[PDB]
Amino acid sequence: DRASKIEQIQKLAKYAISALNYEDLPTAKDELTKALDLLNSI
Amino acid sequence: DRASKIEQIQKLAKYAISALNYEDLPTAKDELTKALDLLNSI
Amino acid sequence: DRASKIEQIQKLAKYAISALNYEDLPTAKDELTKALDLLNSI
Amino acid sequence: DRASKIEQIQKLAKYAISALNYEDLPTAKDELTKALDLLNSI
Amino acid sequence: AILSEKPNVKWEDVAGLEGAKEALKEAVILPVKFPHLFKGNRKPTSGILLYGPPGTGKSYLAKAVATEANSTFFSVSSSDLVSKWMGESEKLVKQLFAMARENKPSIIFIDEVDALTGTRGEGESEASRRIKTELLVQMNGVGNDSQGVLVLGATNIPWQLDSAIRRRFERRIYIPLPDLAARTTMFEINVGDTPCVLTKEDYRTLGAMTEGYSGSDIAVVVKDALMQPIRKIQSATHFKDVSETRKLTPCSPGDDGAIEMSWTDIEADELKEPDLTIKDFLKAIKSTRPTVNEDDLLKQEQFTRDFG
Ligand SMILES: Nc1ncnc2c1ncn2[C@@H]1O[C@H](COP(=O)(O)OP(=O)(O)O)[C@@H](O)[C@H]1O
């Protein structure tokens, strides 16, 4: 972990980006969050 | 705006990703934030 | 007649079809009816 | 459905026509009916 | 006997799955953009596999690589490789990589490599052992110049692909089902110069309606849509004048100025084609089922989840 936690944030922040490509704010505001919380979990 | 605000979040969330590629948590926790706040500004 | 009545039902049932090609239910429900009544008139 | 129901009436009303080409009133009076009822089901 | 083309397809022509896009921009454009970085220990990729469900645009993306390649882009299906005799089935492979090295720098594409693999068991014995053996040894071996040419593999069945050829295709990429925005883009591309009727969020409604298609599915619903108002004109009785001197369009039986006639009755030009609008689109969506299956997607998530 960590080396992966740092890798999963990116995985999240990507999905989030991919989500805004359909204006899906819901998913976005969530993944961009599950990600941030985790960067604090670091 | 908006059509752009939605475009600048992605711009942020990218930089954030690019930042974690040097383990730079500082930048990350910031851009991934300036972005989120803005998705709420939507 | 008859040989024609049988020919006019088809004439109707066609118009009806042609009508649904514009979603015109009104015309349809009518021609598909003027036709049916006539097949009973046979 | 609907976009199809509207398409199946035509499918019916065709068979009905095709049927009268053998003077088969039975089939006709039926398909031209299963169709009409369905245009009311719309 | 051997085909070649410099096609039209661009990266902007391709819509969707940008990780494979930047991967091929790296492994193909990076030898073009910076050949001087690749020297000694740093070597370009020799074997790249694309795979997944059918109709996802792997050959089309290979044509994008072809246009931005500036190289002798070969491409072959299995049909130029199946054994009819007992030995042009193999010498043609030898001449394929031979003339591929003759036209170096070059790119080779093979579509559906699953027809050449599967050494496990003894089924499809002589063709599989001889032709597949020559694909292995001739792909790299004793004195093959593995530099230069690039081997692009496609398939729909990657688990029946043998592990040795799986290692030969050293950089493999899964191609998933695409998303909402890319199919919106392919709708707005494939409508082309035809005068449409809808807006961008209506194409978003279309892509929301069409959850889980392929690129060919989009190509045929757009194709059927380019039959739809023409199908209105070829249908039915009754037209009507509207509005530069006389202009008539199809209308229902009994309407404001509804004459009874056929298209044949109506004068050159002075026809008013129905607008192109969605009800025809949604009717075409209700016309055709998605072809692909989801348990096959579960196996693609199995092999992708492991080896991807
Ligand atoms: N990602 C994509 N972007 C643009 N067009 C696509 C894409 N995927 C498929 N298509 C369209 O689908 C058509 C057929 O795809 P094809 O290359 O036969 O799929 P396969 O991957 O099975 O070879 C192509 O003409 C292409 O225009």
Image (cartoon, coloured by chain):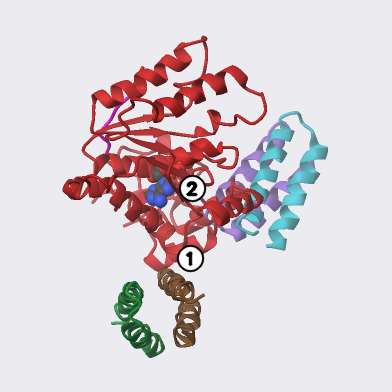
Chain colours: A brown, B green, C purple, D cyan, E red
- In the image, what residue type sits under mark 1? Thr
Q: Amino acid under label 2?
A: Val
Quadrant containing the N terminus of chain E in the rendered view: top left
Q: Earlier in the sequence, mark 2 or mark 1?
A: 1
How far apart marks 2 and 1 lie (CA) works out to 15 Å
Residue under label 1: E205
Disc 2 chain ID = E
**Residue drawn at x 55%, y 39% as measured from the top left:** E163
Coordinates of residue E276 in the picture (x, y in percent): 41, 54
Kindly identify the residue that appears in the image at 30 percent across and 43 percent down. E65
| Camera-side residue of A22 and E254 | A22
Total numbered labels placed on residues in the image:
2
Badge 2 marks a residue whose secondary structure is helix
Q: Is residue E57 visible?
A: yes
Q: Residues within 10 Å of mark 1 (few under 14, many from 20)?
A: few
Q: Quadrant of ligand 1?
A: top left
Q: Position of residue E272 (x, y in %)?
A: 35, 49
User: Do the residues at pointers 2 and 1 share their chain?
Assistant: yes
Q: Residue furthest left?
A: E36
Q: Would you say A5 lies left or right of E241 here?
A: right
Q: Nearer the viewer, residue D10 or A5?
A: A5
Q: Chain of mark 1?
A: E
A13 vs E233, nearest the viewer: A13
The residue carrying mark 2 is E221
**Position above or below: E295 against E70:** below
Q: Which residues are magenta?
A: E3-7
Q: Is residue E192 left or right of residue A7?
A: left
Q: Position of residue E274 (x, y in %)?
A: 41, 51
